[PDB]
Amino acid sequence: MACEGAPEVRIGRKPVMNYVLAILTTLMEQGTNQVVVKARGRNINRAVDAVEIVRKRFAKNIEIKDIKIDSQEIEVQTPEGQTRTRRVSSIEICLEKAG
Amino acid sequence: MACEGAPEVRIGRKPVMNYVLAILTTLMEQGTNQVVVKARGRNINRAVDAVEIVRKRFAKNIEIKDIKIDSQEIEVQTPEGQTRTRRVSSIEICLEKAG
DNA sequence: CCGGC
DNA sequence: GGCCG
């Protein structure tokens, strides 16, 4: 799990543009050369899109250092009953400045 | 640059269990040592879900050999003449039998 | 009947 | 993800 200690940008439901800008501004911070993008479930799609937009359109000197996926089961209390079985996946994309 | 030549499992819009099954069956083949799961756009999180189900629940010894993301330009066509580029992300997850 | 709504 | 054009 590279990018240890690197700042983190968690992807949510806001327009992908916001996260693209978040990644760019973070990598602009003095002494910061890495950023890890994290997302869970459906947001994983947006996380990948943001990274590709960053690399293909804003900064070609940003490399995809590493990518890791994982998951976990959460408790989803049924409507009126009691039971839960839901596994939520996650992705962590480690980005690094100027390869 | 790995998993070259390995059989593939294309994630579509069908339920995730269908692809979990496809991965397990592809793996059951005597010769297949690796399997590459591929997905584009909104199917990427489904690809990660399918792989996580497999790894956490059905083949706990399978290893994620490598993961790569990319994107391709799509020239769509507006209901109104004269369209333009659009970006679609993709992912490739190489799975490898324990050993 | 393929792609948009 | 089935109805619309």
Image (spheres, coloured by chain):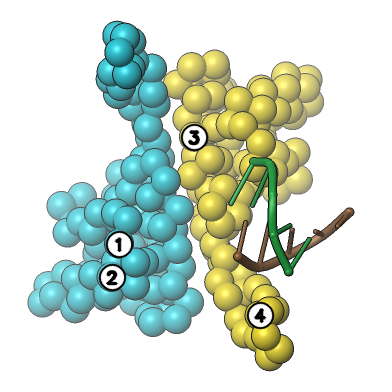
Chain colours: A cyan, B yellow, C brown, D green
The front one of A83 and B6 is: A83
Query: Which residue is the extreme one toward the top?
Result: A82
Q: Is residue B27 visible?
A: no
Residue A22 at x, y = what percent? 23, 70
Question: In the depicted view, which residue is nearer to us: B3 or B49?
Answer: B49
Chain that bears disc 4: B
Query: Residue A17, relative to residue A87: is it above or below?
Result: below
Q: Which amino acid type is marked by label 2?
A: Asn
Amino acid found under the numbered disc labelled 3: Asp
Tag 1, which secondary structure?
Answer: loop
- Circles 2 and 1 in contact, beta carbons < 8 Å: yes
Tag shown at residue B8: none
Q: Earlier in the sequence, mark 3 or mark 4?
A: 3
- Which of the 4 image quarters holds residue B77? bottom right
* Residue under the image location 33 percent in, 17 percent down: A78
Q: At x 50% / y 25%, what residue is drawn?
A: B53
Q: Tell me which chain the residue with mark 1 is part of.
A: A
Q: Are marks 2 and 1 on the same chain?
A: yes
Amino acid bearing label 1: Lys
Q: Secondary structure at mark 4?
A: loop
Residue beneath disc 2: A18
CB atoms of marks 2 and 3 within 8 Å: no
The spot of residue B23 in percent (x, y) is 66, 29
